[PDB]
Image 1: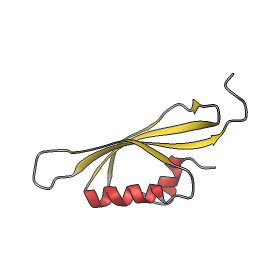
Image 2 (image 1 turned 90 degrees about the horizontal axis):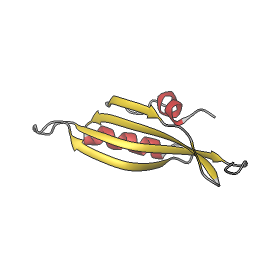
Image 3 (image 1 turned 90 degrees about the vertical axis):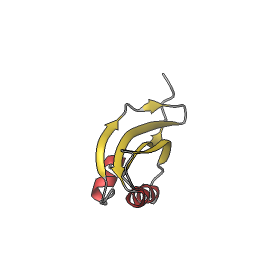
Image 4 (image 1 turned 30 degrees about the vertical axis):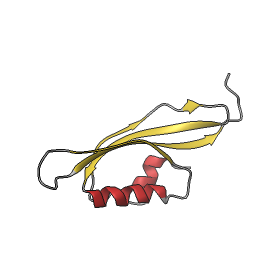
Length: 98
């Protein structure tokens, strides 16, 4: 199954947004599942950022979102925002924690 990075790009997510950083982190084993985290920083207006969050939220797969941060990039009038978020997908763990 294609990863979250591909889902964003295959379905065309993030219109109007300027990606700054995409970092795929090492998988984290837990006793019931393996987490696949992706850290993303992206710049845009509130509307385009919201559309992106809704797009990820509407994917037909379990994605959890964490560590949401948003700050204006500059003190100017109505300027764009920098949004940081950690997204995770999951797969089963049938092998324990050895």
